[PDB]
Image (cartoon, rainbow, N blue to C red):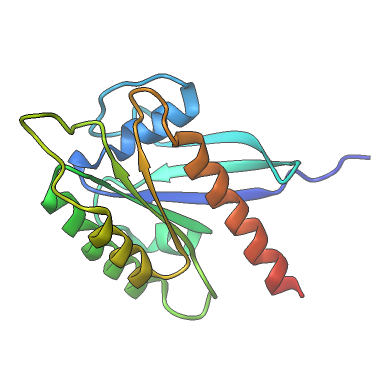
Length: 176
């Protein structure tokens, strides 16, 4: 008989400078492109999670999350640029917006916070330290922190794989 390939819904939020679109594109294709928006609206990718195939659905929002997004996501990945304070501050705002839309009837939301390294240079140095970033992670709940280098693929697969596993683990706990 046919056996279900379960679906996991991963949303991605962040400002235009965040690198969120390049992050998604790199995960899907294995290649780096500089993007302020993903080329396509939605992606899907079959992945092994703890040795079982899942269908991972991935969608970024252009800006503030909307109601549909908030009621759709199993997990949300927040992204900011490590060399842009405004990008980092945008995450706080986006998280508040998400929370107020989603409400408290849906149980825990698996999260990631991702600081991207791709725009760091001698002339645009890192300005967000990992102490401040990990303080925010702690504030957001059910959150893990990563720094990524989409240019060369550093930590990219890990973010999506680990977030997917978080969703599976949480659902298992809820079932019991």
